[PDB]
Image (cartoon, rainbow, N blue to C red; front, side, top):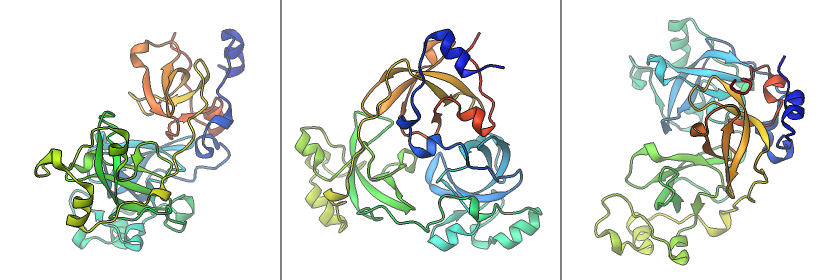
Length: 315
């Protein structure tokens, strides 16, 4: 009953054109073959470097809710069917990764064939996954290389970092000697990474590894020699152009408080690479910043075309 067309007329508003989004945020014609109970492998959003056995706990449109086998439901999380952060059963074994076992197991004595028999479940068919490590790796980025990275939790901090994982065309950025809980996946065009030496050339403070001896006398050349690591080469960095979203443009965005819901939204403010989302009809107290390439923002009509409910403006 609620329609974008009517709403736009009503508000004398415009939608953010589909051209402003990445193809993966816009595609609506792909079918979601995931079914309840199917098992697979995937990264823990809270520990991006770790892989766990997951089960499809719910399906809604082109999205699915995943559950950490053996764990409580409050670890549950939602992803889109085209997420590059989930993989087919057996992926870890085939790509040299480590798989954390279900709470109640030793990865040491874990095998899919049998876990499946023991749970009388089916593994999600591999043709559904966009990432299976068949595609080309990011050019110039290899596990072990070092670089400088913005701690997206503390934007004022640019720190000494390392590439700790590489999957399909993305890599994992880790903050040297810090918790894996500040790590994040990204690609060569990320505006949050810079080559070794960037802070120095920019007159900005570089945060060295935690507890590095004599912190303010940190020398990259020295650190690279101590670790024998290479710096990601400068040619590998290809930062993306700033986005073209304009204030007042409307779109759809997953609700950050209740991930199951997606609401009608508007662009409240903008920066070169992030937009500030406002949920129509709600308090601006809920407005939040989000990267323009985040998988949870979509153009108007995404919910309708994918079969997902859309929450109309609060009234």
